[PDB]
Structures are given as structure tokens and as C-alpha cells.
Length: 51
Length: 51
Image (cartoon, rainbow over all chains, first blue to last red; front, side, top):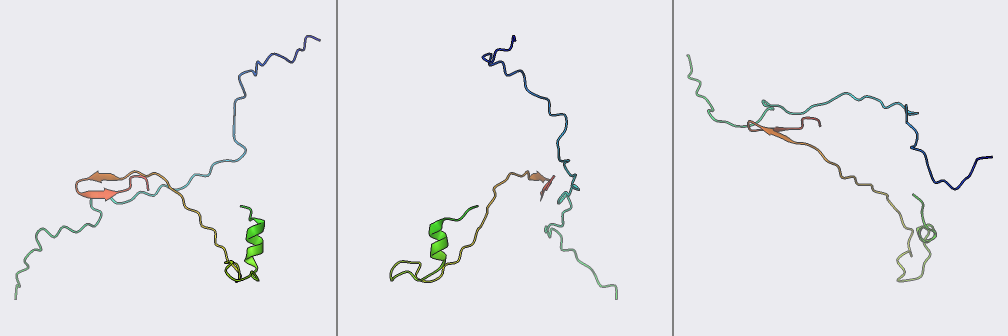
């Protein structure tokens, strides 16, 4: 039948076109930035009383 | 996870003295994970660009 079983030729494989289960998309949540409420107390200022 | 026969028989007490399982025994499963992350440092401010 021209159908031998010996050849280990396992082809190339199979292309996974899609996945059975879709991947949900979560909302991106960043974090602190340059003015991320930090303590530095350089000046402490001086508020003169007007009256 | 699957428990062991020794655990399931030591859960019930009744063991002789100096055997440890003389009293009923309770078990708690704990799972710990270790991951990666990225920390961005700029102008004296720290935050997670991705979080």
C-alpha cells in the first residue's frame, strides 16, 4: 500500500491558529509619578501676619 | 493536593503517650509565590511604571 510506518518524519507540527479560551483584557493601573506626594520640607516658609 | 494516610489517621487522636498525635491534629495549607517587577527612579521619586 506504499504506507510504511518506520519513517520517523514527524512532519513540522501544526499551527495554533487560535486558542479555545479568549484572554481577558485587564485595565492598566500605573503608580506614583514625579509629584507622588513626598516629604522634602526645604523651606517650611514664613507667613507674616498681616494684622 | 492529596493528603496521606498517615495524615488522615493522625488527624484523629487516641495515640499513646509521647507519640505527637495523642490529640487531634489540624492542618493549614499555605501557598507562596515569587515574581518579578520593575521600579522606576527619577527626580527623587519612586513608583511602578506598570504595577
